[PDB]
Image 1 (tube, rainbow over the protein chains, first blue to last red):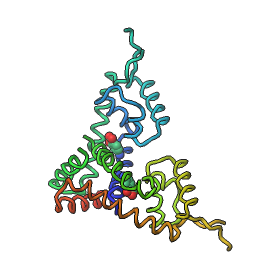
Image 2: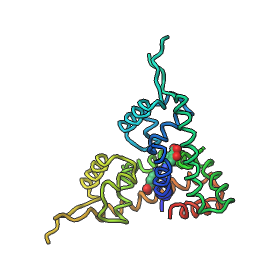
Image 3: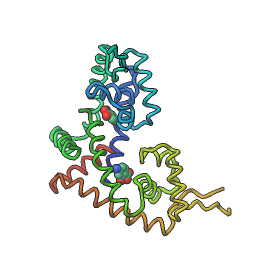
Length: 130
Length: 130
Ligand SMILES: Nc1ccc(C(=O)O)c(O)c1
Ligand SMILES: Nc1ccc(C(=O)O)c(O)c1
C-alpha cells in the first residue's frame, strides 16, 4: 500500500462529496479550485490551476472562460497588456459560499475520525506538505 | 485550507521524490502506477489506470504501449479476442524492485513524523479512504 495509493483513495472519497456539495451553487470542483486559488494567488498560470484541479490545461482554460463569462473572474486590459485574472465582487461572494459548503463536505469526510484525531491528522498533513 | 488542498500539497512533495527514486530503474511514475495496479488487478481500463496516475487516457495508452514493448506487460490474443493486460515474469520482477524503491521514497517523506505518528497517520488514511 504505497503512500500515494492511500492518498489517492482518500481523494477518491473526498471528490464526489465535494462535487455534490458544490452542485447547488452551480459549480464544478475545477471551477471551485480556480476560484479559491485565484482568490489567494491572483495572476496564476492555468497550468498551475490545472495541476491543482487535476484537469488538463485546455479544460482549465474552459473553466477560466466560464468563470469570466459568469462575472466571477475578470482580466481587465490595462490602460497603462491585460491584467492577470482576479475575482470580482461577485466572484469573491461566490468563492465564500463555495468555501463554506466545501468546509462542511470536508467535515463530513473527517467525521470518520474523533475530534483529536482530526486535529492530529491535519497537523500531520501540514507537516508532510510543508 | 480545504482538506483537498492539504492532500494536494502532500502529493506535491511525494511525487518528485518517487519519480527520482524510480529514475535509475528507467521508470516514470505513470509507468510505476500501471505496473503496480496491473499486478494487483489484471484487466483494468486505461481510464482507471489514468485516473490513478493522474494522466490523460492517451498518455496512459502510451504508457501501456511502452510497458508492452519492454516485455513487462502483455496482452496475448486468446486462442479460445485478446487477453486483458497482465504482467510477464519480467514485469513482475521490475514491479518488485520498483515497489522497493517507492517504499523507501515513502519512508523518506514519512520521516517528518515520529514512528507512532506514522502508524497513526497510515491508519487515519485507511479509515478516510475505506
Ligand atoms: N505520487 C504517487 C501517486 C500515486 C502512487 C500510486 O501507487 O498509486 C504512488 O505510489 C505515488
Ligand atoms: N477533492 C478536492 C481536490 C482539491 C481541492 C482544492 O481546494 O485544492 C479540494 O477542495 C477538493
